Amino acid sequence: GSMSDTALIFTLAWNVKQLAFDYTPNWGRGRPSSFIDTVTFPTVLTDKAYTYRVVVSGKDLGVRPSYAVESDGSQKINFLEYNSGYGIADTNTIQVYVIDPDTGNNFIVAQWN
Amino acid sequence: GSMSDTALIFTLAWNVKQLAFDYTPNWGRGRPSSFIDTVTFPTVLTDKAYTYRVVVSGKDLGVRPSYAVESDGSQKINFLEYNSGYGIADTNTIQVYVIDPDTGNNFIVAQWN
Amino acid sequence: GSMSDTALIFTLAWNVKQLAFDYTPNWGRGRPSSFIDTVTFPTVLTDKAYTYRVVVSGKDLGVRPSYAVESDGSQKINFLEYNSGYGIADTNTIQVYVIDPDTGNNFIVAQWN
Amino acid sequence: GSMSDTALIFTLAWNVKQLAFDYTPNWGRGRPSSFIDTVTFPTVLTDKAYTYRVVVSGKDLGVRPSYAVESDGSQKINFLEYNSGYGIADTNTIQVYVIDPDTGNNFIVAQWN
C-alpha cells in the first residue's frame, strides 16, 4: 500500500531544518530531434557523490561518472556516455536511477516512454 | 534506532518532484527582552491548513488558530495567543508542534531551552 | 500526496533486520454494552516507554500512565482512566494517539466513529 | 544525516496495521566450506514478486528469477544461479539487493565481507 508523506516531511524537517530539491526531469533532444540525448535535474542533492544508472527498454546500460553539480544547482546525465556515444530513439523506454554511494541503492528519478 | 534519510528523500523526490522547506526556528524576543514571544519558520508547507500546539515546561497550552502563511513563505506562531496574552521567560522549555489536519498527528518543529 | 511504502520498509529492514508489530485495534465494550471502554493492540513496539493520548469528539482528554506491555506482546488503553472513570458512548468519535517520549510526537493508532 | 525511525514505523502501523518481516541474512556455505553459496531471509515481504541482484567485489552479476517464498515465510537466493554455477570465495565482498518491481529500485538487504 501507500501512505501520506506528511509525517515523513515533518520528520525530515525537524532533523535537517532546510531542504530544497527539484528532480523535475528536463529531457534534452539530440540529433536527430527524435533522439533523447540528455536529462537534467534543476536542483539535486549535494551531500554525497551520487552517480546514475540508465536502463533503456529493459537493457541495463550501467553506470558512468557523474558530470558536476553546476553553480545553478543542476546536474546533467548525458545518455551518449551510457549508450556507446548515441542518443536514444524517443519510442524507447528510458529509466534513470540515482545511486546512493553509501549503500549501492538505486532510486528512480526519471522515466521516459 | 535511526536510519539514513537518503532513501526517503529520493522516494519523496520521485513522487513530488519539487520541494522546498525551511523550518529553522527564528525566535522573537518580546517585552522584556528575556521573554520569548514568537517563533517564525522561513518556508513552511502550504498543502494543508496546518495548526500548532505549544507546550511550556511540560504544560500543554493547547492549539490556537494559525496566522497566515505570508507571501515570503513564512509563518509565525505568536506565543501570546497561547499563554493568556504573555510571552515566556526564556529559562523555560518551549516546544512547538505542527498538527497534520488529516490525522491529528503532532510533530515537533521547534524547541527552546 | 502519498507514496508507496516499499522503499521505507526495505530501508527499515536493512537497519533493524527484524520487526513485528500489530496495531489492529481491538475495541472492548463496557457497561452498558453501547459504551466503548478499552482498546487493545496485539503487538506493540517495546523499544521506548510509549504513552497514549485520547481525544473524544474533538475534546482532548490528555495523557495517563501506560498499562504494561503484556507477555503476549499486547498493550491495553483503558478509557476509564482518561474519561473521569467512564466509558465512551459508541456514537462518539474516539482517537488514540501514541506518544514518542523522545520528541513528544503524537501518532494516531486507533480511531472509532 | 540520519533520523529516528519511530515516526516512520507508527506511520506504517497506522496504514498497514500488521507487519512482520525478518531480513536477518542466513549465509549458507557450499563446497568447499570457504565458499558462500546461498543467503536466506527468514521472513520476506510477499506483497510483490520481488527479485534480487547480486554484486561480488564491485562486479554486478545481474538479476535472476526468484526462488519461491516458502511456507515458513523464507526466501533463498542461490548465488550459483548468478555466478556461472559457482559459489563465492568468502574473502570477497558480496552484496544482495532486493528489487521493487513497480519501480526498478534496488535496496541492500545483505552484505558479506
Image (tube, coloured by chain):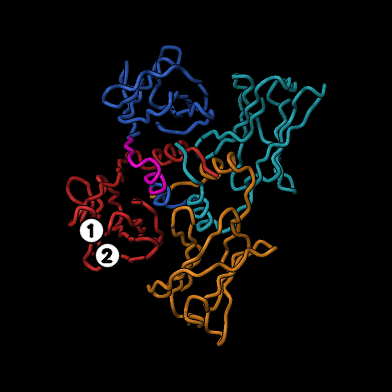
Chain colours: A cyan, B orange, C red, D blue
View extreme (bottom): residue: B32
Q: Residues within 10 Å of mark 2 (few under 14, many from 20)?
A: many
Q: Are marks 1 and 2 on the same chain?
A: yes
Q: Residue furthest right?
A: A32
- Residue drawn 47% across the image and 33% down it: D107
Q: Quadrant of the N terminus of chain C?
A: top right
Q: Which residue does the image show at 68% across and 25% down from the upper left?
A: A82
**On screen, residue B48 above or below B83:** above
Where does the magenta region start and end? D10-21
Residue at the location (34% across, 24% down)?
Answer: D75
Determine if the magenta segment contains residue B81: no
Q: Position of residue C98 (x, y in %)?
A: 34, 56
Give the answer, above or below, for where B47 lies relative to D27: below
Q: How far apart in space, not on screen, are marks 1 and 2 (Cα)?
A: 8 Å
The residue labelled by disc 2 is C82
Mark 1 residue element: strand
Q: Amino acid at mark 2?
A: Tyr
Instruction: Name the residue rendered at 34%, 31% in the picture.
Output: D25
Q: Name the spot of residue A64 as percent of width and height, x first.
A: 65, 29
Residue C10, can we see it?
yes
Q: Is residue B47 left or right of residue C12?
A: right
Q: Amino acid at mark 1?
A: Asn
Residues under numbered marks 1 and 2 in contact, where contact means CB atoms less than 8 Å apart = yes
Residue designated by label 1: C78
